[PDB]
Image (spheres, rainbow, N blue to C red):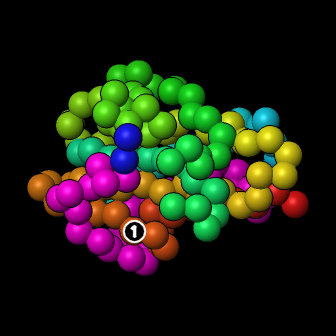
Amino acid sequence: CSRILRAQGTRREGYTEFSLRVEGDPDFYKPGTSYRVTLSAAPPSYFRGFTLIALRENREEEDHAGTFQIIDEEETQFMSNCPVAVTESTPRRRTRIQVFWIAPPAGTGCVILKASIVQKRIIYFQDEGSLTKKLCEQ
């Protein structure tokens, strides 16, 4: 599929009012361990849609680390447009979203989880910042 899935995006680098983080906040990952990933929207702010992927550091095809597992089928789904991505299942307002992610085999290096966010019309995305989480193996 594509990260060219973006054609209507506004790039917004840095820390924003939207945050992608992992519950427990691990400094490092452990191959085959299932971490809970959450996408959050701070004080009087909300989102209506999003996307989510994982990638090995430095890599920009089939270079996606680990696998996602759906927790809330009323909120999330795998995108039939891009199967390696997790996205919203309804454009209804949310302040939180959660998904499982399972750590890739021993010695896969560093992994970045990236999210994009649509609030009203605008789709926001970035390479570095609060919608981005890098996790390494050691």
Vertical order, 78 against 112 (above or below): above
Please give left or right for residue 105 compared with residue 64 in the image.
right
Q: Is residue 134 visible?
A: no
- Chief SS of the magenta region: loop
Residue lying at the far front in this picture: please name it.
61
Please provide percent x and percent y for residue 71: 52, 26
Q: Is residue 90 magenta?
A: no
Residue lying at the far left in this picture: please name it.
121
Please provide percent x and percent y for residue 8: 17, 59
Q: Residue at x 66, y 40 (%)?
A: 66
Please give left or right for residue 19 compared with residue 102 in the image.
left
Q: How many marks?
A: 1
Q: Is residue 9 magenta?
A: yes
Q: Crowdedness of circle 1 by 10 Å Cα count: few (<14), some, many (20+)?
A: some
Q: Residue at x 58, y 61 (%)?
A: 59
Residue lying at the far top in this picture: please name it.
73
- Give the quadrant of the N terminus: top left
Please provide percent x and percent y for residue 128: 49, 73
Q: Residue at x 84, y 52 (%)?
A: 107
Q: Which residues are magenta?
A: 3-29
Q: Name the amino acid type tagged 1.
A: Gln
Q: Nearer the viewer, residue 104 or 119?
A: 104
Residue beneath label 1, please? Answer: 126
Q: Residue 42: name its quadrant.
A: bottom left
- Look at the numbered disc 1 and give the secondary structure of its residue: loop
Q: Is residue 106 visible?
A: yes
Q: Nearer the viewer, residue 122 or 82?
A: 82
Vertical order, 62 against 107 (above or below): above
Please provide percent x and percent y for residue 89: 30, 29
- Give the quadrant of the C terminus: bottom right
Vertical order, 74 against 29 (above or below): above
